[PDB]
Length: 134
Ligand SMILES: [Ca+2]
Ligand SMILES: [Ca+2]
Ligand code: NA
Image (cartoon, rainbow, N blue to C red; front, side, top):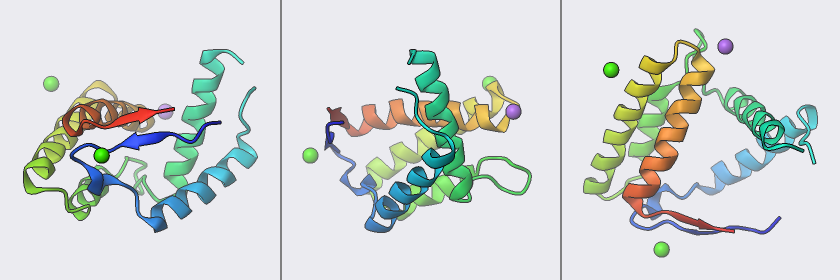
């Protein structure tokens, strides 16, 4: 269980804050109590990962009363990071583009956030030059 080295490229401002790191450690710790990790197939690991992720989003208030992911919360959290204005523009464009694809391809609110997050993970890493080394 090696600690990753992250190169944040042009997006160092996206680094999580101390409150976010402390929260995420405790929220995921609690989710794993009731959704323990297997230690088998890729399919089983992924399902367990996705279940822990939904549990973590709900614990942090990421679904509104209708159960829809809070896309507008995500958008505002990007702006609150205070990226360089040109980089902020590019990151907000990908938020809007990924949201539109997710909500067109899926009616299911969980499938929507999985597609949105997959789309943001790929596109934000490319624009920012983010590299994770384990
Ligand atoms: Ca760097
Ligand atoms: Ca379309
Ligand atoms: Na569903």
